[PDB]
Amino acid sequence: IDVLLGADDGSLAFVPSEFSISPGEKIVFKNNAGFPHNIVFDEDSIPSGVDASKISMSEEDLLNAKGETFEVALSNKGEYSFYCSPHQGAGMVGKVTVN
Ligand SMILES: [Cu+2]
């Protein structure tokens, strides 16, 4: 599943921001507009026992180029909340459910 980092109108949003996937399904987060961006899973809002560092950028890491991606596949079932650190208060957040 492809997720844009920044909308095509420049909005600071993940597109889509809420979605569901199955285990091992690739998520490709792709810099689109308004970069740098990152994608950080909130360590307090992911499934039991999951290591956020296996699945996340750090808050200091950035994707700096249009078209640059961060790929991750999730395995454990449940809800995962994530955000772009520099744009979180602007609303650049999302939630993926693994079912
Ligand atoms: Cu951002």
Image (cartoon, rainbow, N blue to C red):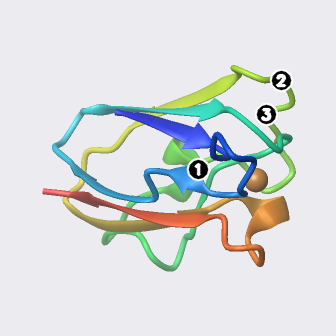
Q: In the figure, is residue 56 to the left or right of 27?
A: right
Can you tell which quarter of the image residue 80 is in? bottom left
Q: Do the residues labelled 3 and 1 touch (CB within 8 Å)?
A: no
Q: Can you identify the residue that label 1 sits on?
A: 53
Which amino acid type corresponds to the residue marked 3 in the rendered image? Leu
Q: Can you identify the residue that label 2 sits on?
A: 65
As measured in the structure, the alpha-carbon distance from the residue carrying label 2 to the one carrying label 1 is 22 Å
As measured in the structure, the alpha-carbon distance from the residue carrying label 3 to the one carrying label 1 is 16 Å
Query: Is residue 83 depicted above or below 56 in this figure?
Result: below
Mark 3 Cα-neighbour bin, 10 Å: few <14, some 14–19, many ≥20: some
Secondary structure at badge 3 equals loop
Front one among 99 and 17: 17
Which amino acid type corresponds to the residue marked 1 in the rendered image? Ser
**Quick one: label 3 or label 1, which is nearer the N terminus?**
1
- Looking at the image, which residue is at 51% across and 44% down? 54
Which amino acid type corresponds to the residue marked 2 in the rendered image? Ala
- Looking at the image, which residue is at 58% across and 50% down? 53
Give residue 84's position: percent from left, percent from top: 70, 58
Q: Can you identify the residue that label 3 sits on?
A: 63
Q: In the figure, is residue 26 to the left or right of 10?
A: left
- Looking at the image, which residue is at 86% across and 30% down? 64
Give residue 38's position: percent from left, percent from top: 72, 47
Give residue 62's position: percent from left, percent from top: 82, 40
- Looking at the image, which residue is at 83% across and 40% down? 35
Q: Are marks 3 and 2 in contact (CB under 8 Å)?
A: yes
Mark 2 Cα-neighbour bin, 10 Å: few <14, some 14–19, many ≥20: some
Q: Do the residues labelled 2 and 1 touch (CB within 8 Å)?
A: no
**Quick one: label 2 or label 1, which is nearer the N terminus?**
1
Front one among 68 and 99: 68
* Quarter of the image with the C terminus in it: bottom left
